[PDB]
Image (cartoon, rainbow over all chains, first blue to last red; front, side, top):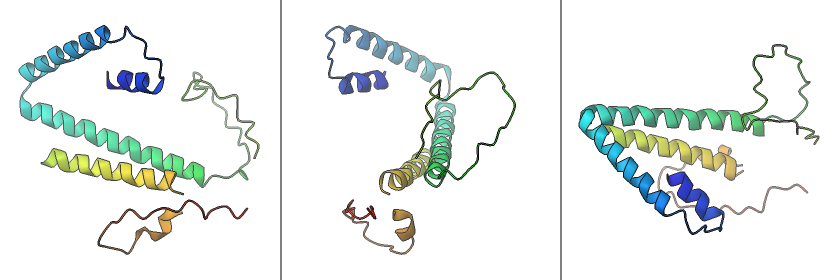
Length: 103
Length: 50
């Protein structure tokens, strides 16, 4: 829901019809949120939130380590041919033909 | 409390990331200065040898 509000703010195209869908989505969240607070104990809900927060920090650290390596990664490295095709995994975005990235 | 402390840690981690990747040369100087964290005006100019 928040991301949708964020995308709309960046793409200036204030499409005038997207407000009614927003409300429904908020209400749906409230109802669901309430159900969660009625179905589970507050200590459990807080513990769950702590765990979810650990995961976010872990992912941020992993990205930094990989991203920082990319900054420290400049081309002598030879194309090692490693083999195995599993599935496809072309790219995180979905595809990666581009790397002509010749310097 | 415990939760808010974890979030602080997460925020700290996010801060370290933003420094390293948006503000290119700073790793060397992080060690010494304890006190007053004033937002040193990151003069962009220096890098390019060129």
